[PDB]
Image: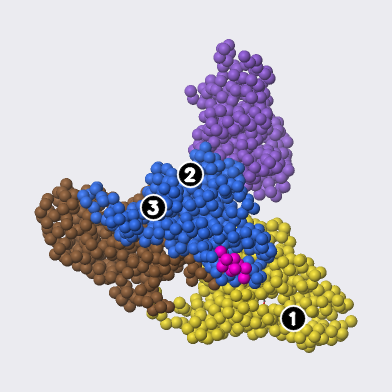
Chain colours: A blue, B brown, C purple, D yellow
């Protein structure tokens, strides 16, 4: 079965006992057991839950892993991933990773004996040079946010492997529909389900999956030990949202192209950051490792002062703080995470252009 | 507003714009701004979650409330307040998962702990180091229901540089308020009595202190182990009957304890409400009642499994604090005074007679 | 075999084919082929010494250089541009000069820190720090640095602990056994011992580091000749006895100096009153012949040194002959005066390399010099 | 919402319950509670004061605003964050009372300062000590209108562990917004351009930073140098015409600068709006306009007092930033010659202002 068919029938997508084409929401905390040391499969909802498990199975099935793990948020998942390491360990970050991941290290992890080194990861040599005797992981994120900066996954993975290093990839922007880091040498993949996977701006969730059984034992342990689990209703809604991913990602791509092209041939606009443009640095690398480009695009205007007047005069893009939803979103990462980030939604392309038009006419 | 009225109308229990007597569920990740510069992003804040947070703050007399994906998610973020190189003092019978947090997650993140009997006040004195930054209390204890003087402990804690953190899961806010007794931070598993219907996994933390509130607020948002709006809403709904439930829990538990103690095959009963309990007077002092938690040791240890496996009403299972009665053997589940034969009962709200008849029939099988 | 026996029979101390109890001097640049090829890559006289120093400091490999500086240069040639290094504030002027004048122009960076204060090193670590250079006891204030502590902290960041072990020789202190990754020596000093050889020695715990050092010894070409290799090895054979005598003499001299009305402060790790005496005792099996002392009147330091007739007014140290210098007017003349006082180096500070002469002759020379001020 | 609009509807410009287009004046000291557990005590919080604080936060791009009894009391509270044994860099011509605050109040409390020319970015680099915590800028500067590059000094301070503190009184939030140029704390003397009507003594402070906001709040409350409700309200009221007043101030000030410059009897003229002014290109870049503040030194230095005492429209008085024209010799009230005349150009008719100057010049040699 193909990706499109897997989004609908993958993992667990059916109640085995009733035939329900939808996995039931197990709003429960505990489970009755036959004799002690002989359970019915589930013991306690923090450790495992049939609804959450179905979702965890789905994301594993999609990214080509052995196990999935659903979390209360993207950050909670990432946090649990880094709980695999001791104090005295080192991690190499990309120079433009998501701000909350930076704050995770800066303010939570570093504090606990975990050191990081920020480097440009599209500069393969900057990673070669940055490894210390205690470096235990390489944390990549491509396309990056904002700026959509592409990193070479297979290369970095190869390089991380001949050193005793973990390749941990944040696949949020380019979904499992467009990119599968585990098939390119990654050990652990993390998403914000809060974004595209959910895709209706109505769930806060993180998903992690892995290629490695030993890694999976570890991640499980810390999901259970720290307990930042995804609830069953959210799990169910995430899975429901995931069902449409393919169609949504297609529509996201189609729209964001029209938007990028229109923006590039504009008098008010200077540079434009989108992976689908032949004009974007490493465009070739992208077509190599991505089956498509999402709906994210940063960009800048020649007049750097108007940035805030432009964003605030738009009437169809929602001025808000997330991305990856069916509604188009807009931000300015200066005060949020003269650069303007667009999360192109799945509204009619013309209405999106007409909305950008009228907001340009105003500056 | 008294406790029993507060449970229903406390924190935010109403929708202000619409008038709705229930808080609406905000299944939403992000909010439109008229910005740039109330709500911005659901991990940082959410109206459903907030209403519950205000509720629990209101019930414990804290300045802020914090809702987590699980009890443990809450405790974890509480200990994220500390730097590597810091020292923590622990109870010798703290909940199994709390001990595992330190042993498996927090020690390897550079924190050190020391296990002392918290009912022994001089043991806490003797165990204090220069890097000791906090004392962690759980009373009554899981699973032996051991009682610890909260005023005394917080007193000794306060006149060193120490934080007094209390897990108040067993007594809930209906029967004990550690903040009003000198504690700095209070943590619950909302999965237990607060939800009460064994259908939600949830943590709740609250604090006396405005600055401490900012720190927890920081690590709630930064680590991101937040309760979802649906679970927040359901947990709030559960809390509305907390008062009535705890009374039934206490009435039944009292009845059961007095049955088990008078029973031929039983050796000791651990229940704070039994006059013969170590620190029974101290319980009456710091608690407005005892919950539904008790455990007992049966004269012949080898019969504990067979006893537990032949109960027909009590559900053999992992958790506690629900309307349905639960039973476990701590030795083989959640995990000094703990013998393989120890049996822990979570007395639910069924008919006292239905619960007694169940135990009667199970003893007849050993 | 124990350290004292190891100075005589360790590394390679014997010619296997001929039986000679002294390794032959291979004054050759090349070798016929049908395990040596070129003397800049490998030479059996140098190799013998190399094995010895590795064997004494408990290393996997040794590397003999044309000079102490040459070795320290080879070590720091490991790091790429962008890398940052932590240096002790009492670092050898030439080591400080290497960074200031050679390595910086190549893309390195440093920060100067008092290494006797462990929190200072913590405050100074950057994400791009790769190394920590330690030197204990220090010149000229003989200030002690907790080797194990500093090695450990450095290890739990991504750092290589590099220790200059010249002053307290492998006979009294073994950094690699206390968490150091690389040990460097100026063989010019106590190791050779007869002020007649200029040489560097470098050894390491780590096979991978050893391949790195080996490569740079060879590619940069600052190697030690076979004659000097042999001379250095000969000197090392009496390292034990000489150190015993250095220390005996030094203790005696230090004790004399603090009995002394004109002398203010004496800096010697073997004195109980020395800051970190207890730490000294933990990581050192003894103290060297190195000491300084400040006298109450600064301007009297010139006259004191000038009237000395046994101590030789000289620049070096660690030989069998006693040496005297005034760090402010010799080893540190370039540095602005008010900065020298900032770093504890008064114009009245006098450094002695206490040699192995009869202690009484050494003391009678000090008495007559005092008697003349 | 644009700045011109924001001055009228920003922060809180309306009573929520009643719909009043003006914020009501809460002459109250205390509030009934249904406690134990919004407003508790007027020193901690007052709805009127808060309205003004929200407005300034909103104007400067801050997260919180803070209203004080005076510009000084605010500056005080800002520096109250620092421990003893800390170090601070000061502009060589910061406000006379800002120096007297450090010189005589904060120093004896264990604080240390170094006077530097901040328009010399290399000079600040030369003065950083290991114990230095903050740089304090003031541009344009009193009374020479010396301009400092906010963006660079912020950067230089940002890559060290330093706090950028800016006194934005002169070029108001309408012309300059330091917080967007990498500043951490902005402070105003509300007594000046913000009130605009020379009838309120006030100080306003705002910040980019949550943790700094917690701190400033703490010290505003603990020292208690808070602004009253009536003064807050009058201040907010004043702020509503800020945009209109600043435009007229500039239009007049440029008109005067060009009169004084082309004048035979005048020597130098200080005004950021003059092309021939140190760092004029810098002014244009970080400021959206030049204000009503200008100074000038005349050729006959001893006849400075005679000039000032013969002005009929301009008022010889002790302040600035009002709708009426003010004049003072900053020396009587390092650049400052005992014949430097400082002009606070009001919003009166320029012809009337110029005709007051003509007649004053026509009485000196
Ligand atoms: C990449 N990784 C991680 C995150 C954090 O996700 P969450 O907000 O669900 O914690 C985000 C934010 O959307 C992102 O773009
Ligand atoms: C006391 N504290 C904490 C916990 C942990 O809470 P949770 O299981 O909801 O994470 C439990 C058990 O649930 C308990 O009895
Ligand atoms: C410590 N290390 C290294 C050196 C440099 O050694 P060389 O002069 O043999 O290069 C010296 C002084 O020469 C020293 O005292
Ligand atoms: C610049 N900063 C600060 C102040 C101090 O203001 P106040 O005297 O109102 O406290 C003044 C004087 O108005 C000024 O011109």
Residue located beneath label 2 in the image: A183
* Vertical side of B222 occupied by C86: above or below: above
Number of labelled discs? 3
Residue at mark 3 to residue at mark 1: CA–CA distance: 76 Å
Q: Nearer the viewer, mark 3 or mark 1?
A: 3
Q: Nearer the viewer, residue C28 or D104?
A: C28
Give how far across and how far down residue A209 sits, in percent: 43, 49
Around disc 1, counting alpha carbons within 10 Å, would you say few (fewer than 14), some (14 to 19), or many (20 or more)? many
Whether pointer 3 and pointer 1 mark residues with C-beta atoms closer than 8 Å, the reply is no
Residue at mark 2 to residue at mark 3: CA–CA distance: 21 Å
Q: Residue at x 52, y 62 (%)?
A: A345
Give how far across and how far down residue D356 sits, in percent: 81, 86
- Which mark is on residue A9? 3
Q: Is residue C373 visible?
A: no
Chain identity of mark 2: A
* Vertical side of D339 occupied by B187: above or below: above
User: Which residue range is magenta in the image?
Assistant: A349-358
- Does residue D137 appear left or right of residue B88 in this picture? right
């Amino acid at each position: 079965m193909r990706m499109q068919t897997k989004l609908i029938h993958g993992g667990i997508s059916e109640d085995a006992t009733t035939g329900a084409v939808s996995v039931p929401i197990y709003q429960t905390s505990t489970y009755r057991q036959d004799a002690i040391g002989r359970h019915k499969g589930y013991e306690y909802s923090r450790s495992g839950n049939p609804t959450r498990f179905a979702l965890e199975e789905l994301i594993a099935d999609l990214e080509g892993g052995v196990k999935g793990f659903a979390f209360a948020s993207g950050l909670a998942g990432i946090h649990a991933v880094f709980s695999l390491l001791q104090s005295g360990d080192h991690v190499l970050l990309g120079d433009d990773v998501y701000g909350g991941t930076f704050r995770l290290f800066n303010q939570v992890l570093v504090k606990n004996g975990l050191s990081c080194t920020i480097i440009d990861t599209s500069d393969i040599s900057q990673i070669k040079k940055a490894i210390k005797p205690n470096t235990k992981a390489l944390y990549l994120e491509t396309p990056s946010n904002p700026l959509l900066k592409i990193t070479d996954l297979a290369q970095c993975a190869s390089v991380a492997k001949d050193h005793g290093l973990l390749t941990i990839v944040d696949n949020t922007f380019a979904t499992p529909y467009y990119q599968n880091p585990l098939l390119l040498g990654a050990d652990i993949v993390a998403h914000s389900g809060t974004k595209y996977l959910g895709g209706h701006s109505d769930v806060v969730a993180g998903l992690v999956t892995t290629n490695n059984e030993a890694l999976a034992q570890e991640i499980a342990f810390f999901q259970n030990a720290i307990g930042g689990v995804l609830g069953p209703q959210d799990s169910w809604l995430l899975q429901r949202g995931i069902k449409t991913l393919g169609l949504r990602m297609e529509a996201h791509q189609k729209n964001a192209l029209c938007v990028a092209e229109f923006l590039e041939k504009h008098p008010k606009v200077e540079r434009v950051y989108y992976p689908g443009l032949p004009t974007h640095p490493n465009y070739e690398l992208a077509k190599k490792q991505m089956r498509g480009f999402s709906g994210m695009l940063s960009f800048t205007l020649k007049n750097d002062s108007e940035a805030v007047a432009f964003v605030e005069s738009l009437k169809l893009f929602i001025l808000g703080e997330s991305l990856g939803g069916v509604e188009s979103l807009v931000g300015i990462p200066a005060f949020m995470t003269g650069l303007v980030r667009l999360s192109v939604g799945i509204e009619h392309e013309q209405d999106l252009l007409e909305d950008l038009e009228q907001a340009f006419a105003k500056i």
